[PDB]
Amino acid sequence: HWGYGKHNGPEHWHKDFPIAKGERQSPVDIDTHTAKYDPSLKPLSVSYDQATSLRILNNGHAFNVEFDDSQDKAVLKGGPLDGTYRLIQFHFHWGSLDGQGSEHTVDKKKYAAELHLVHWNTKYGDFGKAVQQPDGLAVLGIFLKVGSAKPGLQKVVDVLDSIKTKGKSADFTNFDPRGLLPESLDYWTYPGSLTTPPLLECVTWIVLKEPISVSSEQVLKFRKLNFNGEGEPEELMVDNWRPAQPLKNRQIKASFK
Ligand SMILES: [Co+2]
């Protein structure tokens, strides 16, 4: 299958997923000297008070913290978006070294990791229908740098041992995703894609300007996860990021001067 390894990584994905070479692929480099302030944008509305997390799953590529998306419980609105987008899951991308791991870059800077909070547009009824639409998803992306610990990430770090290998899951109720956000909601936005196969061009990206800090210990525990299943040779789950793709005929807009 596709992955991040030596012979199935991002540079191969186009063979099975030709849209990998499409017009609106993600991630991209965010050039802060060409992104333009857009006064038509509004503030983001992140409404996560009623979020219902359910489960955490190692899917062999990353791990997903999954939410109940059968009601408007944890929603994203505003910003560049029209309508209401429901949180379905979050996951991360991270490196083997603190100098790489993010998917988006900022003036070519790579962060240690990147958090993706994935939301789907309720007008399309379910996730699977939403990914078939150009405005089906909204992904809130948040950079991680290594520095101080992020207290609100620790409950995630402490369950990772229970989902070491591909296909393992664990109960993960009562997790508050608000504890993963930086102070500021200033953002960049542009139209793009999922960053894993099937690479569908269905995403309004909203990338926060302010990174969150995590500790070296927290990142190290991410790097103990495994791509492989139980009883297979160990392959550490690191460097599960796609590199920046060509911007093509797109503009990145900023919510801030
Ligand atoms: Co992602």
Image (tube, rainbow, N blue to C red):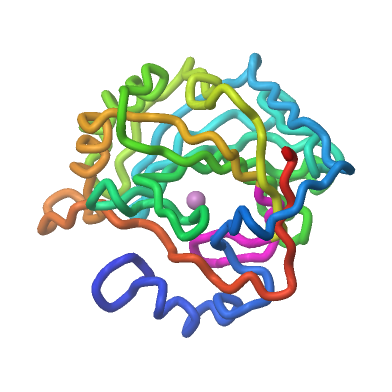
Q: Is residue 130 visible?
A: no
Residue 150 is drawn in which quadrant?
Answer: top left
Left or right of 61? Residue 220 is left
Q: Residue furthest right?
A: 40
Instruction: Pick the residue in front: 247 or 60.
Output: 247
Quadrant assignment for the C terminus: top right
Q: Is residue 210 above or below residue 247?
A: above
Give above or below for 91 relative to 110.
above
**Left or right of residue 162, residue 42 in this image:** right
- Magenta span includes 151: no
Write the residue at 52% across / 39% down.
Answer: 142
Magenta segment range? 192-205
* Residue 100 horizontal/vertical position (percent): 33, 54
The quarter of the picture where residue 133 lies is bottom right
Instruction: Please tell me whether residue 156 is drawn above or below residue 207 in the rendered image.
Output: above
Residue 220: x and y, percent? 20, 37
